[PDB]
Image (cartoon, rainbow over all chains, first blue to last red; front, side):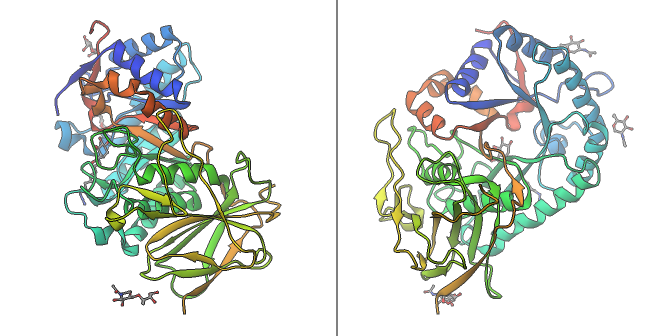
Length: 384
Length: 74
Ligand SMILES: *[C@@H]1O[C@H](CO[C@@H]2O[C@@H](C)[C@@H](O)[C@@H](O)[C@@H]2O)[C@@H](O)[C@H](O)[C@H]1NC(C)=O
Ligand SMILES: *[C@@H]1[C@H](O)[C@@H](O)[C@H](O)[C@@H](C(=O)O)[C@H]1NCCCCCCCCN=[N+]=[N-]
Ligand SMILES: *[C@@H]1O[C@H](CO)[C@@H](O)[C@H](O)[C@H]1NC(C)=O
Ligand SMILES: *[C@@H]1O[C@H](CO)[C@@H](O)[C@H](O)[C@H]1NC(C)=O
């Protein structure tokens, strides 16, 4: 990797894209600009901050990406204490800028191996006062070696749980109550697993990661990437949405901010994975008190889910996602309740149509599939 | 037998996620593509992007630490 320059024009393209799309831009600053005694040289950042101020851009900041691997990447070692001081200096610069209340996130460390955990802990000791959220990264697999079986394996899915617990151990020991974000995450690193990261099969990992993150206390999850060279993109090089885009859209329309819990009775919680939130209140079809269950079936047969009292007779809407053939789980097309999801045109997303179930019926979840279910008139007071 | 009983905890919220809980990145390396302006200018891509609002868009990647801002550049 070599140094490269970018222009005011590039900044404007990026900001405009975010602003016109209703997204909140977070811009990562170069942390490898060091002085004589290996302090962060902030002068280039100053130039950028000045330019963004002048244009009136509302932007949040990070500093560095995966500092745990700077030795590998640039043959420079920066310890967590120093990094924390570097964030303190950025925070002073932001406070002297025209957006003095701009948010700062970091340190965008990798998953918590011993050396990374140490770096994170020393960073939070030093710099943890000035960050608005702790960011860390997670990947399940190496894109070069990942297999299809890996994408379907509950033991692979389960590994994320230990990473989350380790990060929270570091955080509770240094800055308890600080928010924790996944700042970069996907199925597989090295740009994704060819013919797997861009398919229906990628959804088992992504939907589970979402479920677990929400359940375990992660506040925001940042998907690597929306659009780009890597196979883990939500949108391919033709600007066409892949199955994870559709899953992500459905998730956003159905799943609320209040996180609850679901679990399956019996000693086998591995292959049938279930999550429960309040329904997204901004959804016009649903009302205060409704619940959104989501479930992943990694068994090779259909399972039939029974809702507990007092929800066993309620009207439920199904939103079942299944691949369009002939390529099965390796398909790049998906059907919602048997209707292929496709843009209406370049300006128009289709409607996401429910399938009402017979009140009192068990919820059918075919083998190797994922579905959302909205329990209408659930009248859950915690959601209201 | 393929019938499975679910238990639900509904007394109170266990956590609260951001409305932007499901967020996205654009890798910093995409700014080295000669066609950066065309790509992010695509109305189709903007439509898909709007679909995921509200969300954070993190501009970052391995390349973050190999990018230098140049106020002179065209
Ligand atoms: C199907 O999966 C089997 C192991 O899963 C268990 O048995 C099946 C029939 C379901 O009842 C599932 O809920 C159970 O957990 C394997 O032993 C079997 O080889 C698989 N069949 C295939 C690949 O055709
Ligand atoms: C994050 C990075 O910021 C992106 O620019 C990369 O494109 C992305 C990716 O690899 O797709 C991602 N890099 C993650 C690198 C994680 C490597 C883990 C190595 C583990 C080796 N040791 N052990 N065990
Ligand atoms: C910081 O960087 C600029 C530009 O690369 C350089 O001219 C300046 O002397 C540096 N400052 C320090 C303290 O090293
Ligand atoms: C971390 O690095 C700094 C800067 O090089 C150094 O001065 C300091 O002693 C190191 N801290 C620890 C705890 O080793």
